[PDB]
Image: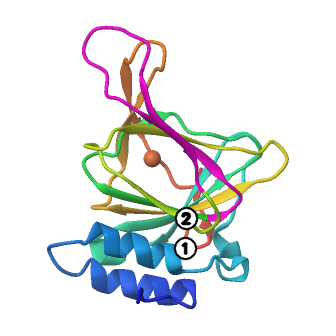
Amino acid sequence: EVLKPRTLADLIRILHQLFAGDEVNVEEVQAIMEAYESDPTEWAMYAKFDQYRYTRNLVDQGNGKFNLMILCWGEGHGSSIHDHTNSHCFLKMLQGNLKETLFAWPDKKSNEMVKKSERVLRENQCAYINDSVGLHRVENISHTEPAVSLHLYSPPFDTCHAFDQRTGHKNKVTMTFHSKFGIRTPN
Ligand SMILES: [Fe+2]
């Protein structure tokens, strides 16, 4: 009975409705994002890759309620261990596979960080995280194929923290966009 978007445009339209109000049903959003069947013809214009690290490509600003973006992971590309600045964060696979490792939060004492969960996100799967769930790292499982993911963050945010797996120490990071609406940013 899950509402199934037939196109990415459909999905965006639904998301505008689901985030219009004050409450967001996380499980409902997750199921509808998962139900969209990734179609590369519909998102190729956002899939702009870089040789050395993943790229963040803005798709939609959600009437200020969320950022919707596509992240392009080249061969072997991965993220830092990071938090999500008190937002809801949905991650759906569009191509390939990402390994998600969930980490416990450090305390002030320096220590090796503790893994709480490790999984591979399957085709079209939508995962969910917020700061109460934990920290995470995501990485392309493949050194021969890319991965592409669709991220919805609500409310939008432009900074987070990256964490050193050896110590738990963190640094603030300002996130930048490689492209917006299919158009490369100045860089
Ligand atoms: Fe993340």
Classify mark 2 as within 8 Å of ligand 1 or not, answering yes or no.
Answer: no
Q: Residue at x 33, y 83 (%)?
A: 16
Q: CA distance from mark 1 to mark 2?
A: 24 Å
The residue that disc 1 covers is 181
The residue that disc 2 covers is 125
Q: Is residue 92 above or below residue 15?
A: above
Of 23 and 53, which appears nearest the observer? 23
Residue 83, quarter of picture: top left
- In the image, taking residue 41 as reference, residue 130 lies left or right, namely left
Q: Which of the image's four quarters has the N terminus? A: bottom left
Q: Position of residue 163 (x, y in %)?
A: 42, 26
Q: Residue at x 47, y 74 (%)?
A: 33
- In the image, taking residue 137 as reference, residue 163 lies left or right, namely left
- Amino acid tagged 2: Gln
Residue 42 appears anywhere in the view: yes
Q: Is residue 156 above or below residue 183?
A: above
Check residue 105 for magenta coloring: yes
Q: Is residue 44 above or below residue 133?
A: below
Of 17 and 58, which appears nearest the observer? 17
Check the image and name the residue furthest to the front: 1
Q: Position of residue 108 (x, y in %)?
A: 25, 13
